[PDB]
Image: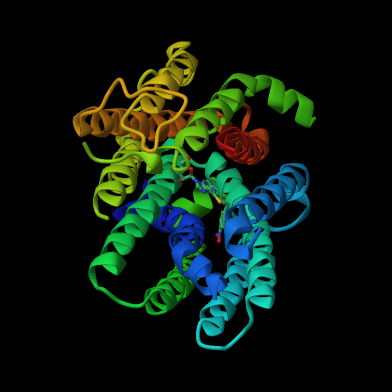
Length: 365
Ligand SMILES: O=[N+]([O-])c1ccc(CSc2ncnc3c2ncn3[C@@H]2O[C@H](CO)[C@@H](O)[C@H]2O)cc1
């Protein structure tokens, strides 16, 4: 078992990048959607409708994959999901240049979001089921790719604000970049069968869940907390146009990406250590901490940590805990079960992850 040139690993990393870089960009273009709808109102309900249509299909299709991934080849699932996402994003880019009233644009945007989240649900689940067969480092690879997707999203946001370009132009660029990335990801995947390291490892749900129940609930809780606090609540912090982006999104994405990466080479406390759920639980402390920072306009709660340094430090620790512990759970879940089931376990984990998102999306509401 020799991953020459780390090829397989690299590819998996790229794959991770491709799962969030398309959708992450879609979340970076929210200003553009709301500004085009400006032309009760659609813009005012846009975010809520988007979260609904994103988390419900995501959850449903991740569950269906957890149940039926064995029934469809992984090549089919992966390639088809990627092609569907690419086509949807190409249509998204086209619509930027075509005239369309606010209501048809709103509805078509929500349809594209439903399709993105569905196909990407199956794609993500299939990717984590695949990486479950490979060493833990190769699930850490997917997590690192996701972290880099977030990092690129943050940098692109900052540059779109700095470039002084029109929201339509910057959003067009976002969509085209996402399409190019999806093409690159497809190419990367197609280059897997030709790697002997990839062919070396490619050669009852209640029970599998009971075996990985601890780590599954762990990742679910991690993302519950994270999405309950980030970004809905953290974006309301004010200094005591570049403060919020840089101090919130940039810091979070940087430290989350680096944490997700560290799990590739350093995997403490391990898969059987009860310290991992303990740290996951300890992450609860970020709810009071982050809620008591310099939020404005503040009404029902005070500001105990007014200086921005508190906000930056809590953001660093929060994002890094998120990344590191989520990667550890995703890596150890498939390793807490026999080989013939590691593919299901992974898939199962991919569901709970999304659950942690959905619940978080509800708690942030
Ligand atoms: O291929 N596709 O087009 C595609 C693939 C998957 C999806 C599901 S969306 C998703 N799936 C996993 N993880 C996410 C997601 N959205 C935010 N996150 C993480 O939440 C943490 C903060 O709470 C951050 O670290 C983020 O990485 C949509 C589109």
